[PDB]
Amino acid sequence: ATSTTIAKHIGNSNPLIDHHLGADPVALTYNGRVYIYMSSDDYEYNSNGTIKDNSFANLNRVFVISSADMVNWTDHGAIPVAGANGANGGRGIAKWAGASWAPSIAVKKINGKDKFFLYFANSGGGIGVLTADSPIGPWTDPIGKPLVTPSTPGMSGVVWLFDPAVFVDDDGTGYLYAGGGVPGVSNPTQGQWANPKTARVIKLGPDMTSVVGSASTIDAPFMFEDSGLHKYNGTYYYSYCINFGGTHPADKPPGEIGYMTSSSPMGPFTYRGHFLKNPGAFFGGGGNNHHAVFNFKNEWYVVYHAQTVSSALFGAGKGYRSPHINKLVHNADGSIQEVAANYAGVTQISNLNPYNRVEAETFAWNGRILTEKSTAPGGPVNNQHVTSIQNGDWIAVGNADFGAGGARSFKANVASTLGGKIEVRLDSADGKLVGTLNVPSTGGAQTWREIETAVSGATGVHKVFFVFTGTGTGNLFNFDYWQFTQR
Ligand SMILES: O[C@@H]1[C@@H](O)[C@H](O[C@@H]2CO[C@@H](O[C@@H]3CO[C@@H](O)[C@H](O)[C@H]3O)[C@H](O)[C@H]2O)OC[C@H]1O
Ligand SMILES: [Ca+2]
Ligand code: NA
Ligand code: NA
């Protein structure tokens, strides 16, 4: 193992991923997994190949990763949401949309079946929705135009009609929160900074792809963007990013996550405080806050973004954002403690079972690979593979539990022009070697075989490292999934 981690270091849980970016995260919790959906931040370049600042040019997909344990993330690739103009090479789903910013996600049981709803902003003018029968697609545009526009009743007044947050209440009623911006164009007055009156909530129809009635204004003091809604102990918590302009009182600090409570989903809301500092307070930082509060496996968390990967690569964030999660604590009085955002992140919640098929693109740490959509036969929806594998690269999973009996063999599904090796190591990238898998030439990068090799000494709970070696100077092979067999 020679390659180093970019930003998510072995033993740490933030950023969630560092083999690519992901901005504006939101969480769905569903049947033992947490799914994180993100705007498609993607490095932009000058014509001479040098990196430039993020201009949001490429925000036309939604990236999706998921975990059962907070440490190992399955990369589910990208949903080609935007279909207008050039976007997504004709494969875009929402043909009316040139952009798909800042996703929101909901599940609702309809006609005895779980149905999933992905919301997004077509830049600053309109919210769209796609539907699917699984949290990872495939996705359908059931409307063919925006769900919400400035003409939706109650939506006039909104400066930036974006950053949707959709919540399905306990009674099954869906609600959409959206909006932000500050009125007064180039020079808002002090009062316009303090009360933009640009946040909205509107009830959704039963189908989750329509609205009922008109939108209500939520008077979020110093509103900026990044609506969020969670419900704790019967109270609805509307959270949002506080703006950066005007003078601010001590209790509404610029760029921080403010929150309000109500006994009803549409209000009236009352400001209660703030619980997440600007990312640059912790990682410095740079730039805008975006967040979502969620409960997964019976603990409260917040997912948010920071410029921690681009920072480590370039020596500046440059507007490129990565997801992080930390714990969130409600007090006895219903108030929320300041979130202690950091790199350590959340300690692994459960062990990984190495005797099922595990996607190669399910990993906790890597140095340094990419994931992309795979040509491998079979596999889960939107199956990906690990690629850009060179000599000395590796990926690793957290706490695989081999059990006291331990493993007998190791299978890997691979595609290779010239061949190479996968070393299986415990605990560290130079750790106990339990097996070495020889990847043959298979026919090339799109031709697949499952290879088996012997394993010995794999028992108990260990980080497992897959270390890639070979004589080539570029990509050695593509790696789709693996599985151990029990002794
Ligand atoms: O002070 C800085 C802030 O301005 C910054 O917030 C960003 C402001 O621009 C927003 O992008 C607009 C979204 O709406 C579209 O219609 C417009 O075309 C966009 O320009 C963006 O949402 C914010 O993140 O954050 C960093 C602060 O220091
Ligand atoms: Ca795969
Ligand atoms: Na969001
Ligand atoms: Na690599």
Image (cartoon, helix red, strand yellow):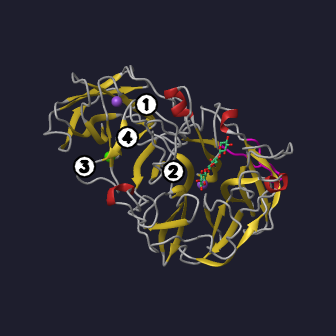
Q: In the image as oriented, which residue stretches furthest toward the left?
A: 443
The crowd level at tag 4 (other Cα within 10 Å; few <14, some 14-19, many 20+) is many
Which image quarter is the N terminus in?
Answer: top left
Gap in angstroms between the C-alphas marked 4 and 2: 28 Å
Which image quarter is the C terminus in?
Answer: top left
In the image, taking residue 250 as reference, residue 82 lies left or right, namely left
The crowd level at tag 3 (other Cα within 10 Å; few <14, some 14-19, many 20+) is some
Q: Which amino acid does label 4 sit on?
A: Pro
**Circle 3 residue:** 375
**Circle 2 residue:** 38
Q: Which of marks 4 and 2 is in front?
A: 2
Rendered position, 212 above or below 395: below
Q: What stretch is highlighted in magenta?
A: 327-338
Q: Where is residue 219 in the image (x, y as percent from the top left)?
A: 79, 62
Q: What residue type is labelled 3?
A: Thr
In the image, taking residue 149 as reference, residue 373 lies left or right, namely left
Principal secondary structure, stretch drawn in magenta: loop
Q: Nearer the viewer, residue 205 or 432?
A: 205
Residue at (43%, 23%) from the top-left corner? Answer: 4
**Circle 1 residue:** 50
**N-term mark: 2 or 3:** 2
Gap in angstroms between the C-alphas marked 4 and 1: 41 Å
The crowd level at tag 1 (other Cα within 10 Å; few <14, some 14-19, many 20+) is few
Q: Nearer the viewer, mark 1 or mark 3?
A: 1
